[PDB]
Length: 265
Ligand SMILES: COc1[nH]nc2ncc(NC(=O)c3c(F)ccc(NC(=O)c4cccc(C(C)(C)C#N)c4)c3F)cc12
Image (cartoon, rainbow, N blue to C red; front, side, top):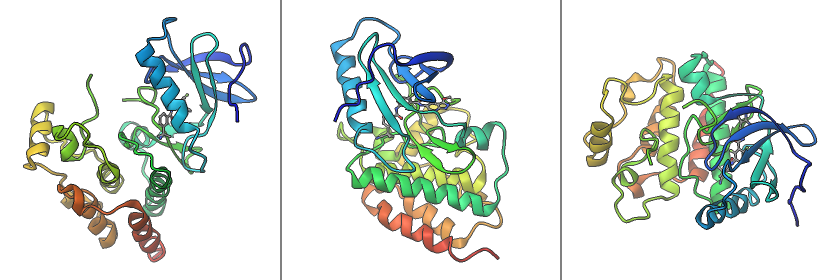
């Protein structure tokens, strides 16, 4: 098939924020959309390989909890268009406006997110950057996973969600399904404590270092009083410092659809 969206069809609008490659604008193309572009006119053959990669990946995804890729554009500048999500990122809800979710909606946001990663994984896609910033609550329900980049709030990197092996840079390709599972674990941790990990440490390098040596890990004793003992039990199985001791998502997903089935009281 062809998803090439011809020249002049897209109508760029308000500037939303900086995207992986160029900048993300909220535009129009048969309804509101997001357009991520390249600001410079020069296609670095090392950048185009990336655009031609991102488009290559979104194209494989088609599911309620992954952001909807709707089409790409090569004509002036290179762009990738996704549906426009009305709402905020989970990171925004949790840590900025400090929204207070009830345990049910929480478990659910958790369950959708898991539901989502599962799909990406079944399609043999590693996300490599799952985190509350990249989890979008479209219309306040319906988790939408994507890699929004620097659009959405807040050489560097996002340290908190990296599993140790990653934070080390062991064998040049540290990333795995279990990589994601950890990132998911920290997300669980966020949902269950409304906080980010290691808030009492104000030194990035030390966080990187210790989380790497396995001297530091999330303080699980901060889980909200009413959290189900199985959510907490799962949280840890996901944040295991040993790559191979972590659960993959088909199990994670089920462990959730189980604990979510028994707690309306
Ligand atoms: C403030 O920013 C915003 N508010 N509302 C918005 N609505 C949409 C957008 N939209 C985006 O930020 C956006 C966009 F406009 C175009 C492409 C991608 N790319 C991806 O989502 C992506 C890239 C690589 C891999 C993957 C996944 C994880 C699926 C894989 N594999 C996804 C985007 F995230 C921004 C918005």
